[PDB]
Amino acid sequence: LPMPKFGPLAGLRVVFSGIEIAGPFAGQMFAEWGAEVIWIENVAWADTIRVQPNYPQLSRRNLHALSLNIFKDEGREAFLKLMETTDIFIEASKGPAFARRGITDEVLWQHNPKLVIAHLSGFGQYGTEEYTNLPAYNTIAQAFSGYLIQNGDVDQPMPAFPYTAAYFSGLTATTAALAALHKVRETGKGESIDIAMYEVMLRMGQYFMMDYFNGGEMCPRMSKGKDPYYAGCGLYKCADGYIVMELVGITQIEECFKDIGLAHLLGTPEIPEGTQLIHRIECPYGPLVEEKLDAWLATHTIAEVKERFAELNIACAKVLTVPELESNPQYVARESITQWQTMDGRTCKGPNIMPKFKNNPGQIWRGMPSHGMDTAAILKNIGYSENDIQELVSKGLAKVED
Amino acid sequence: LPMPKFGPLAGLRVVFSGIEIAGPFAGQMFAEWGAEVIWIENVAWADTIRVQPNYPQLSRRNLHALSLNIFKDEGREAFLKLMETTDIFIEASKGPAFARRGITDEVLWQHNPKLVIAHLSGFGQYGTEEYTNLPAYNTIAQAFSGYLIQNGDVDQPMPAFPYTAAYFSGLTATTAALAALHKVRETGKGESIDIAMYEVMLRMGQYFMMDYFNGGEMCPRMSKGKDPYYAGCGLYKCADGYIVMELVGITQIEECFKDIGLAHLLGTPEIPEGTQLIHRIECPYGPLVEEKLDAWLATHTIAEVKERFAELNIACAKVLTVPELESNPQYVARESITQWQTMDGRTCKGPNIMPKFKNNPGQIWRGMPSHGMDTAAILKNIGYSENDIQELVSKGLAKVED
Ligand SMILES: CC(C)(COP(=O)([O-])OP(=O)(O)OC[C@H]1O[C@@H](n2cnc3c(N)ncnc32)[C@H](O)[C@@H]1OP(=O)(O)O)[C@@H](O)C(=O)NCCC(=O)NCCSC(=O)C[C@@H](O)C[N+](C)(C)C
Ligand SMILES: CC(C)(COP(=O)([O-])OP(=O)(O)OC[C@H]1O[C@@H](n2cnc3c(N)ncnc32)[C@H](O)[C@@H]1OP(=O)(O)O)[C@@H](O)C(=O)NCCC(=O)NCCSC(=O)C[C@@H](O)C[N+](C)(C)C
């Protein structure tokens, strides 16, 4: 299929079946980095993402579009021929839906013994009858993993946003596939990978949860963007708006205490000389620390705080709003935000490829394709006759091609 | 170095320098999957994570511990010998700190032309003088990327939690390194990777931000855990506690409207027959929808809602608290939470390896090592004499070994 040769993944053949964020995100990351990536959509329906007015232009770029009923007679027979040339297949469904419908890993490996198979689901490929076959979205994975309960204010739990768990899960699928791809080069044998969204999110929520699993208490939720345990960490207000900061390190603490008027606290039994973090709940002086930090910050502008925090090696930043991003000199300097052309010739704006590969940078070579745009070009590459693909179209096995 | 042969990454040699979450997380994921992973700590100081009472037992497991002043005379000379046997090196610092201190990518490639180098920083390896060399933590990356402003309640922005951006950045580093590792096998030439935390997070926040970049408005923040745009999506309350749900799909909407008493809305100009999502702000009936959903949900228990939502293929889940995770039958069935022994022989509880590799599952083979635990065993493997390592210890170039 005609495509520029670029990125660390040039000439890798990746195929994905899935809607919305998680599976498509996993597959599309391959295409950001120069892989040949085929997006499978249903025949009668199309990927739900297409309902979004702008995002899909970013989230489906560099992709080739396919419409095949991958479960029916000849539609199934081509999917399996396709799999013989594919290095990596990502599928996102309700549990072992592929296996239930006949496309086992064993069936897939009969067509390609080397194939890497990444299964993405809410609850896993196996488990109990109650959960294994349930549908899931980001929010369901946040709820079930204990991530949701950790987010929000003291009195109001809420999801991390936008759709955080869908990005973690898709990114994990990309990572695990690439690791499995490595193993295939070493041994010539394929792999199957069972990525459960709740299990991904369980991991991402362990920083304090590990306290609960090993004798401790669980942490509370943040109060108004402030770290639940650590003073001087999180959302603060200066004289002229919100900043973030992290009071971390021996020197940072010594010098910051001196500024806010707490010099005399340094060297006491509960704050000995090598102290690199202050726990707000364990420390009787924790609230005092907050009171003085808050009071000292409200006196200074964001610019004055930044200048002094730079002198002390204290990490901080202005809380930026979306309209402030484009003109930020760091963004401009690094071309963090760029433009490209859509398939119909409009100009599209949004993030550049990330991260930056030095020797083999990714690039944007195609806009989002339309439903089944390349279904006819792929089936013909897979050896199917000109008439043969006309017969797939008619029987409703292959679709759109508009 | 003595270690079991397992996982898709068996026999891969990975080295990382970094503290807290982001860099160490990137490097440790390799070890979850059977790579030989060397953790570098400073000589006089030790990784800040060690201050946490339990988490490091999970986040530093399967690792080999090294203490070398990687910038001083002979300490530097060994780091570079080590690099000659290393496949992947992950470093997390303030911008191009390694280059500034003399360890360029060019210097590194003179020792190993194949080496994959992953640079993790807040603001990138290059940019403007104002930002490029600034320190960063999760919160700084959330602030600078527009992610922070998207999280929280209508009136109160707050970070996604716990330390969300540190996990995305580290996971991206793992992914990018594995992709670059692939390219080395294809061409025999190494790679350098520039992972800026704000650029990672910019990507993860694009779902609605793409509206702003292309003519639209930016979305508001959630109100009490409810999707800012889409009715029937997010945090809801049943008669006996919090659930999440996603009203998505043609059938799901038709049948749910019928239940909540909104049957008559189906088929109107603004809700035509194929409607798969309802936008709450664009739709005059959006608030009505919420009012009826809320009212119908408050009548039913979580169990009754789940049973009916299963009948209709509507994704949902109980919002679980941490103490509910261990005994969940899906968790138990999949061994999502497991136990292992620490280096000093205590029993440790926490998440199992994720995801599940079928043919080559990861495993937990070692607890977190102590500071410099393996520094003497690594230097001797790298060819340094028994006396030679005694001279490194004394001059303060190599440390702990306790
Ligand atoms: C799709 C899904 C989310 C549940 O929806 P569904 O039951 O309507 O399934 P479907 O894919 O739409 O298609 C229904 C049937 O259609 C079949 N099908 C799908 N593609 C096909 C093809 N090419 N050929 C033949 N059959 C095909 C499927 O196998 C399936 O058959 P089954 O009933 O036997 O399972 C399910 O795939 C699933 O749970 N996947 C795992 C987790 C996952 O990736 N979910 C998405 C997370 S991303 C996310 O959270 C974003 C979201 O929150 C944002 N928003 C608020 C806007 C919605
Ligand atoms: C460490 C860092 C976070 C800023 O701290 P620092 O300035 O104190 O740097 P350091 O690593 O502690 O060491 C200071 C010096 O010590 C040197 N050094 C470090 N290791 C060495 C070695 N082995 N040999 C010789 N020198 C060594 C460093 O090069 C460095 O020299 P420089 O001043 O020339 O830059 C910086 O590495 C950085 O910004 N990294 C990139 C982003 C990153 O990974 N940050 C962590 C995100 S994870 C996260 O967000 C978790 C956190 O939010 C949770 N909590 C609330 C509890 C804190």
Image (cartoon, coloured by chain):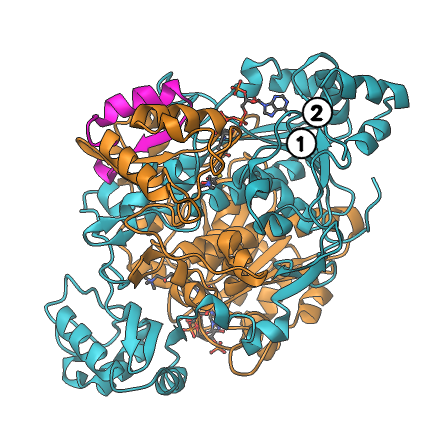
Chain colours: A orange, B cyan
Q: Is residue A292 left or right of residue A276?
A: left
Residue A41 is situated, as x and y percent measured from the top left of the image, at: 44, 63
**Is the CB of the residue bearing disc 2 within 8 angstroms of ligand 2?**
yes
Give the residue number, with chain letter if any, for mark 1.
B40
Q: Amino acid at mark 1?
A: Ile
Q: Is residue A374 at all visible to an observer of this figure?
A: no
Measuring 83% from the left and 21% from the top, which residue is drawn there? B390
| Rendered view: B304 above or below A347 | below
Give yes or no for residue B110 being in the magenta stretch.
no
Identity of the residue furthest to the right in this view: B386
Give yes or no for contact between labels 2 and 1 (Cβ–Cβ under 8 Å): yes
**Residue range corresponding to the magenta coloring:** A297-323
| Rendered view: B332 above or below B230 | below
Q: Nearer the viewer, residue B316 or B22?
A: B22
Identity of the residue furthest to the left in this view: B284
Chain under numbered label 1: B
Which mark is drawn over residue B68? 2
Q: Residues within 10 Å of mark 1 (few under 14, many from 20)?
A: many
Measuring 15% from the left and 61% from the top, which residue is drawn there? B281
Measuring 66% from the left and 48% from the top, which residue is drawn there? A179
Q: Amino acid at mark 2?
A: Leu
